[PDB]
Image (cartoon, rainbow, N blue to C red; front, side, top):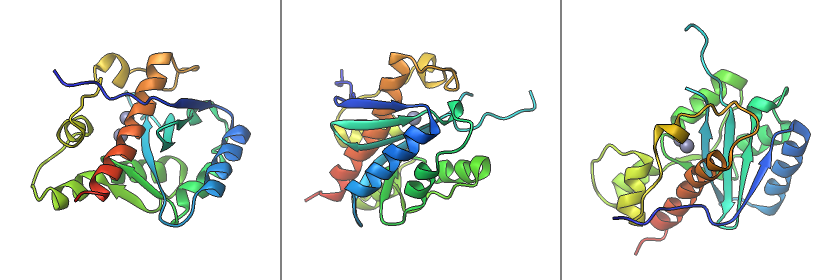
Length: 186
Ligand SMILES: [Zn+2]
Ligand SMILES: [Zn+2]
């Protein structure tokens, strides 16, 4: 039985473009070249495809932002700047796929992403095909709630439920903690 990893800080939920741009600029102002944030995204699972509904940025153990873009009529300009900011790193798992998706859906270019599975394969010197949960178990010795119920819930629904918020925040948080873990190994 492995302990369950959960974001323990404050979750800042933003579903309006202006509010989101303001918070994003605030993040940009508090960070500098070399800094990193935990990053992740969610979206609901005939002919039409589902677009990114939520973007998570965990700047620290005490604060994680959830940007409900599916509820925004215009993509947050401040969020766009932050994401395209090469000075700030975004750590995650399967994050190149996130970048691709962001470009396709909103023509937003995620800059300076850090694929944690590659960092792990090179540091831990192992050739493994990972899942975020699997990486948390091996690196953090913890577990992640991953039942379809929440993982595959309708992320475009407003508002996000308390379970959705904690799950989305925890996925970004896991990225930040794994990044710190691997980046400071000795
Ligand atoms: Zn993800
Ligand atoms: Zn996720």
